[PDB]
Amino acid sequence: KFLDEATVIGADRYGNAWTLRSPPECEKIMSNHDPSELSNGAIKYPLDVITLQQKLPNTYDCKFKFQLLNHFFVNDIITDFHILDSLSNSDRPGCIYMGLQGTVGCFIPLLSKGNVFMMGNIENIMAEADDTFYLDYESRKKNNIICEGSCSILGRDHQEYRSYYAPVRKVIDGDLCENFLRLSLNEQEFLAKNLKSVQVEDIIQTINEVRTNYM
Amino acid sequence: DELYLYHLTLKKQTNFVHSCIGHFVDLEAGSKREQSQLCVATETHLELYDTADGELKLIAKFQNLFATITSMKSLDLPHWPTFLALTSDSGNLSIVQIIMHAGALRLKTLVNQPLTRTTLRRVSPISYMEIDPNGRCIILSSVEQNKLCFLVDYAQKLRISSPLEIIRPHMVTLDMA
Amino acid sequence: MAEKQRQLKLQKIYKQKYIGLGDESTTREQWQRNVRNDTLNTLQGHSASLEYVSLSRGDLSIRDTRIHLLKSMSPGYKAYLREE
Amino acid sequence: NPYIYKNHSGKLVCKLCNTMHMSWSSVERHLGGKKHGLNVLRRGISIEKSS
Amino acid sequence: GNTVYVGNIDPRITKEQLYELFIQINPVLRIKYPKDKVLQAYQGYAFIEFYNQGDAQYAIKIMNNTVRLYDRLIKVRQVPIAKLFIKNLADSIDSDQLVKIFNKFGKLIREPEIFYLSKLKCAYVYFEDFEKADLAIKSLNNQLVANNRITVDYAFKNGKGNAKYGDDVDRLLN
Amino acid sequence: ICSNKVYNGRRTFERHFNEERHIYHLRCLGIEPSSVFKGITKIKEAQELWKNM
Amino acid sequence: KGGVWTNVEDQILKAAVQKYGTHQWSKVASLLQKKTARQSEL
Amino acid sequence: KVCGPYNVLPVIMNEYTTPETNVQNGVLKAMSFMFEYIGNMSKDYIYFITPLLEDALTDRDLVHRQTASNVITHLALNCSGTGHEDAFIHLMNLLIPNIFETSPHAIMRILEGLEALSQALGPGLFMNYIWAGLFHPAKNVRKAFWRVYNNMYVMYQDAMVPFYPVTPDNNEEYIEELDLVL
Amino acid sequence: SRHQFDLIMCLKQPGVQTGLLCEKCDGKCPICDSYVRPKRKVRVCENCSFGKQAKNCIICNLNVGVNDAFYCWECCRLGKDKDGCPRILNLGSNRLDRHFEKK
Amino acid sequence: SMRILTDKAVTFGPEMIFNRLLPILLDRSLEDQERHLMIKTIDRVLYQLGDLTKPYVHKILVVAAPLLIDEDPMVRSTGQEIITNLSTVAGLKTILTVMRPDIENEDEYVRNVTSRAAAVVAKALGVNQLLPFINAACHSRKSWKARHTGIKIVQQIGILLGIGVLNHLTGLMSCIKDCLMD
Amino acid sequence: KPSLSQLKSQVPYPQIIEWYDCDARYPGLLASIKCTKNVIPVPSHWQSKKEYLSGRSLLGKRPFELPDIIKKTNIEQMRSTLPEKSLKEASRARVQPKMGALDLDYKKLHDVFFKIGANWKPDHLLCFGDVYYENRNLFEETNWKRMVDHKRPGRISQELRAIMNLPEGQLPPWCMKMKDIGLPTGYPDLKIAGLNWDITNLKGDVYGKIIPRNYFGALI
RNA sequence: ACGAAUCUCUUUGCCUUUUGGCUUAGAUCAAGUGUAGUAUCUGUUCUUUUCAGUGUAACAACUGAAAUGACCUAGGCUC
Ligand SMILES: [Zn+2]
Ligand SMILES: [Zn+2]
Ligand SMILES: [Zn+2]
Ligand SMILES: [Zn+2]
Ligand SMILES: [Zn+2]
């Protein structure tokens, strides 16, 4: 589906979701010229665009490549996307998808760079919660029981799972961020203590704000 | 100029491919244990049910799991509640307990035993799991060539043996009982 | 000579553990047998990918589709379906 | 010695011949050698054939 | 076709400076401005490629003898046939008399080349066609001109008149 | 294709293809020159290529 | 008991003796890493 | 690590300018240990040291090129998933031509750098550099490329599957299930 | 070992017991020999866990081991924690040659 | 000259090297470092050539097998390394032809070091392959001293394999079981 | 063994196939892999028997130059590395050490990486297909891309005005030929002072001129 | 031709810190090793005409054996 006039969202049959943007070199040409002029030969392309075509003829047919914007392993085959201008009178657009196995999910754009920074920090301490809890248990037995992978139950690294076929690019997983809500207050304060200036009550406020306000 | 996304799962998937019965956790009783409870799983989530009153009651939904669950079977050790043996795409054997902890019913890992590397490989012994009906051993099998057997025991703590191994270089396993 | 001797000795251990390694004299017959057997494991193995293939083939159950993908690893399976 | 230099790593080089030398004693071996001589005898001809 | 020549360049001119002047004329694709790589000094000229032949011929017409760079005036400028060996010629035969003989069978792309062997006068005569030179071999071979016997055959490259040589010269004449 | 001319070096035989003379035997035959023909020597085999071109 | 003189050490001696002279052998030894003052004199 | 890399790194990037080999190799080695010690904090510094790794990868000395790809190993592992693919695509372009090296310390450092780049880039985009060499006519081309394929295969047997260059014309036994549309 | 190319790892299927390092080898990754950021404990196979040898260090093979061995973060990111038993079986020519020159 | 000899070994004959190298290992004047360096040269020579004849397999066992009973454990480990490298080089058919009269020998010393060497051969090539050779020696109504060593081979197999001996327990028990009533 | 023209007919890009591709053990498999979309060719110095990066081009390699954002820390003036102290004075500096040899501003050092240059990127970053080869000069290429952007028809810089002997305010000396031949074909929309633009616009360094939605989820 | 100036160039002559001092040369004192492996000069050697096999991406290299006389103007349906 088209997100804009330069960016498209899509999915494949291996369980991945991704967005692709036309590069700004491409978008300047397509704005300042008529569509017939691409067919004519009356476009002055830069010399490095001309020389990659002679050098890589199987690769550079169209003269431009897409820029991978976002990538995420959702582990379900997505059969529809629905692009919505708002959801229940919220500000943001959302784009909700449906999977073949019965999933409904959404991708919400984050609009503030400070919102992006706070939610990245919540996802990060939830991601190394195995590492943080296990190394604390090992240090007490040095100088005074937790299995490896006790917070993740199965023992799987969360980044590796969401990077199954390709790296994650600029998606924050909210499902990982909502497992913070299920933790007990002792465990919540052990995870939050590395973050500076941020309290447990401010983390829970930030997580809850997505489902009340943003959709 | 970039695009920063936030992902949520509004409704979870409903392709339940694993099921196992037993008595996993005590609910509302002092010492009443009956094999009426039921745990179903998709690839990514686990749901516990109760069938004592003649109908499917949902007891508990659990946290978000980030792995691909490939096998799930009940484990009843001779002379306890029932455990869950799981095998996912992390390359490990997990034995798990359902406990009550600070208000809520939750998952608790007891054993994580490393097998081979992660993801769905044909050499990874995660496709077929079969448990001895007396509770003595877990039999794990890959799609191609590998079979593992773990002797599981309980004395003050759940304990697994080092594995027993079959390597059959070209055999593609189709079923196992 | 000893650094070259490790990488020879480790190529054998990794080829036994993981089937589809090669070197320089791998035939296209050997390489393509690896690519096919890996791909059929994936289609069988991920459960969304099972349902996608079983529905679009129009098979009668999803388990009939799993045994079709696992018997297809055999080189003598095209001739088995042809001798019915 | 109009051809001996130090590069951007401080190693001694001959620009005529594109050689590299570990010390100054290797430079003296080079300049008394026959490869450096044939390269002088080519810059001689390529200057005597075009003014 | 796309490239023009620029001459009379003071080697204080760099590649950056050359590009300024020539985009006032037309948009420029590439510049190659050669250098003796030992003395690191340009040799007084550049090859400058434009996008098409229309912008090229415009640049020659506008910029030739127009601009002075370090008081030096910039120049801008643009940038198989049948062979019969004849042995034992008469020596009374001129190179203009070879043309008078051989025009009746075939058109001459060049003039003939009289060279002396052994005393022995011989000539390389050039024809525009493989078949019109055959008429010279058909009618003039072992014939008596200026009271001397001349022999006409193919000249050597072994000799001309191959089956691959018959095919391609037919296409070249097309 | 170039009158069965011999070349005494394999660097020179590769550089042959983008020269004025090999351009000529191709272009007079009915084959417009480019890298797609920076190959073969035979008169015949460049005709089955260009009729696919 | 070695006392092996490589030819670069011979070049360092002759250049070193050209500078320090013939009576300052401890300067001549200061340029050699592996030779003594009596070894250089000899 | 203890005082902050913003205090240290402008001084050691300046020091790389000096024309001495052991100082330049000491700067690149000190930069390797920095990115092992600071783990995920590396990502704040990727763009600033990408012109210095370009100076070391395009140099004649193998030790310069050993030590540059040892930095790339630590960098690519700690910053995959953070959005810096254009830095690593650039670094992949300068590291791929050293695949034919024969020296044992240099080629094990170059191969470990290639393994970490295929996590920064992903197996599907990394493998576009590798397909052509697998069935090359020359044997030396074919030894060097199968040694990279075998590292990639041990890391991604299942994940390589969407990216194989197999078509029905190319592959006799091509799985007809891949062409089905639901 | 990353450094000595004649050392030979076991790489058998890992068991349930843990491999130990000595005081000289303490804090080292068995794979890459890195001193920093440990992630997961090392499991050795059945045969490497039997008898008098099981108490010995799994890197240097002679001294008695005291603390547990860990894979580092970067070997766990690469999957090298899953390849097999990381115990060195031979002693290696570096160790051997010092032993016989000295007495 | 160690690295030269490893490279020139394949072009020299194996006959030429072991005719000269092996007699040094038998003199009474030899020092501890001199013994080690020549045992080390054998081990580097054996790896490359790989096709080793039955008269030379015997001569190597004469010098290699008494290392297995040396006082210090460093020398005993280098004895085990040669015999396992010679096991893969010579193969199973050749070494058993060599070791067979050496068990029937009248000297107690030779029967001691042959029993120990054959169990290194068993760990290299598998006890299942060595089981009929051992089963013949443990029965062997011809020679009484051949029975005694066939049981010592089994005992050294137990020491070498450790808990690995359970895979072969039924074969190794079947070999020895009647000998308790001898 | 197939011939070269035989092999070129099987593919969509026959310019990718070369003569040694017919010596492959499987030329038909090799040639279709090479013509697959996005497959990058093998680095081309495989044929050569010299050594990667051993050519003459490495003699002209310059020293490292810091990114221009880092030059703002002023470390280049405080430690000079491009071309001292005796052994006694170095020995005396260990027992009486001098402090504050570097006068670096710590707030300026942090703000280089994190405030001034949080969005800093290098000007050249090789794209997807751009594999590095030995005689490639990346310095020329960033100079050339920057030469195309800043420099425009319709302005002439002061450096060229000294060379051309054409000061400001003045028609350039091909003005008359464009009165006789005409306007440039490659600039349809160029307006030149004195031919199709007003002569009082002929002003300083300028004599001519070309006169001819937000993205989803953009950051506020 | 010469009286004759002025610039360029060589030869001859001129000439520069061509050692701060002194004594018992004022006195004394100076380089770790082992295991693996790279890079980089120089000297030295390629006296061969075909063919066959091996070898290579193609070469090369390696292993085997054996070719000379006549004439005409680089060339020979030459003997
Ligand atoms: Zn030179
Ligand atoms: Zn041609
Ligand atoms: Zn082990
Ligand atoms: Zn140790
Ligand atoms: Zn490690």
Image (cartoon, helix red, strand yellow):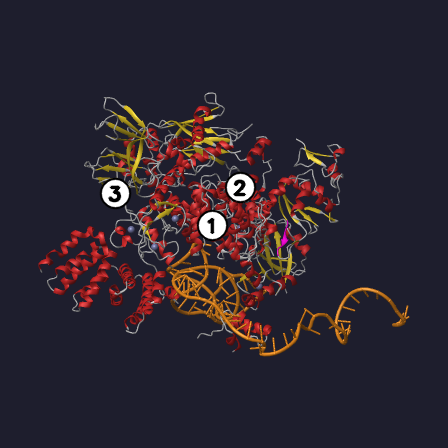
Image marks 2 and 3: residues in contact by CB distance under 8 Å: no
Residue B58 visible (yes or no): yes
Q: Check the image and report above or below for B165 versus E113.
A: above
Was residue E29 drawn as part of the magenta stretch in this picture? no
Q: Circle 3 sits in a helix, a strand or a loop, which is it?
A: strand
Tell which residue pokes out farthest to the left in this image. Answer: J181
Can you tell which of label 2 and label 3 is closer to the viewer? Answer: 3
Q: Which residue is mark 1?
A: H32
How crowded pointer 2 is (Cα within 10 Å; few <14, some 14-19, many 20+) is rated as: some
Was residue E36 drawn as part of the magenta stretch in this picture? yes
Q: At which x and y percent is residue K95?
A: 54, 59
Q: Nearer the viewer, residue B34 or B14?
A: B34
- Amino acid type at mark 1: Ser
Residue J152 vs residue J84: left or right? left
Q: Quadrant of residue B153?
A: top left
Beta carbon at label 2 within 8 Å of ligand 2: no
How far, Cα to Cα, is label 2 from label 3? 54 Å
Q: Which mark is residue A53?
A: 2
Residues shaded magenta? E33-37
How far, Cα to Cα, is label 1 from label 2? 37 Å
Quadrant assignment for the C terminus of chain K: top right
Q: Nearer the viewer, residue H124 or G15?
A: G15
Tell which residue pokes out farthest to the top in this image. Answer: A89
Beta carbon at label 1 within 8 Å of ligand 5: no
Image marks 1 and 3: residues in contact by CB distance under 8 Å: no
